[PDB]
Amino acid sequence: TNPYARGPNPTAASLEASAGPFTVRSFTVSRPSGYGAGTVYYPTNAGGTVGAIAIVPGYTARQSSIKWWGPRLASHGFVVITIDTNSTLDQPSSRSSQQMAALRQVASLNGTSSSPIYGKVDTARMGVMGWSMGGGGSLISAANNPSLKAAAPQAPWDSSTNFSSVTVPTLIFACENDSIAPVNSSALPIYDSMSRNAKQFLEINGGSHSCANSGNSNQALIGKKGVAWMKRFMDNDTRYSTFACENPNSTRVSDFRTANCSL
């Protein structure tokens, strides 16, 4: 038995719903250490300790842009911290440092008896997500921290597109009609550069730069893929191999690629 498997056996319907099986609670981090602000989402009675995911917004943006991932991921068995950065103008490298500082504080809170997540986290199993410059920061986090178990940035941008060192399983959400971080100069070159990992490229048909943000029109598919990826690679949970690695064969997807990802 896989010691990290949590929750009921997945179905397409349960992964496409607005929330999974677990009840979610949240709190604001009182004294954030190394980043601007944080909200922690966590499940009640997930059946064991769970991995932690840190999510960072883009340039000029705040937690609201990426908030929907908190309850969505937490309700399937993850502790999620969404952050504001020290300044909304921080660059991707600074976003990566703040993302890792947020994970370090979640690990610290796991050992803090007064914290609602006391004893709820497996601090050896962490993942990174983020939008735009926060997506580039997530790739920087993966490159610099290969002990991370999964990355799933959305519409990523960085000055450099070369992430060939990344060995962390990485799902790239891309937005077909992005005019801010255009797919052909950002998300797709980033994806192509990664030769050392399990990876996936999922481009949302007709999507603008904000196509995976809170309030987007593809939460069923995007949330299914995000949860399935984190389940498969943070929990080593082979019940999610098909969901994580399959082509959706959906009109909502304009481009799908995957490598080293077996059904």
Image (cartoon, rainbow, N blue to C red):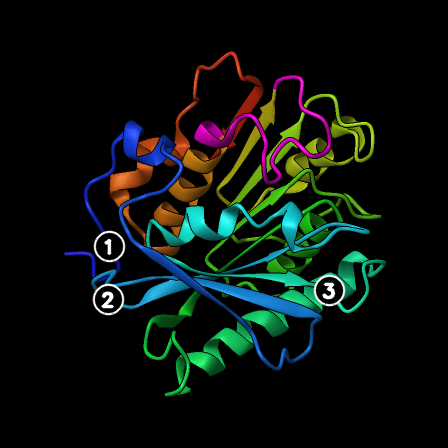
Q: Quadrant of the C terminus?
A: top left
> Relative to residue 226, is residue 47 drawn left or right?
left
Percent across and percent down for residue 154 are 63, 40
Residue 179 screen position, x and y as percent: 82, 27
Q: Position of residue 53 (x, y in %)?
A: 49, 59
Residue under label 3, please give it: 85
Q: Secondary structure at mark 2?
A: loop
Q: Which residues are magenta?
A: 205-221
Is 173 placed left or right of 227 in the picture?
right
User: Label 3 sits on what residue type?
Assistant: Thr
Residue picked out by circle 1: 6
Q: Main secondary structure of the magenta part?
A: loop
Number of numbered discs on residues: 3
Q: Position of residue 84 (x, y in %)?
A: 69, 62
Identified at 40% across, 86% down, the residue is 114
- Disc marking residue 48: 2
Callout 3 touching callout 2 (CB < 8 Å): no
235 relative to 256, above or below: below
What residue do we see at 36% from left, 79% from top?
118
Q: Secondary structure at mark 3?
A: loop
Q: Amino acid at mark 2?
A: Gly
Label pair 2/1, CB-CB below 8 angstroms: yes
Residue type beneath disc 1: Arg
Can see residue 248? yes
Please report whichever mark, 1 or 3, sits nearer to the chain's N-terminal start. 1
Q: CA distance from mark 3 to mark 2?
A: 31 Å
- Mark 1 against mark 3, which lies toward the viewer? 3
Which secondary structure, mark 1? loop
Residue lying furthest bottom = 113
Q: Please report whichever mark, 3 or 2, sits nearer to the chain's N-terminal start.
A: 2
Q: Is residue 209 magenta?
A: yes
Q: Nearer the viewer, residue 123 or 90?
A: 90
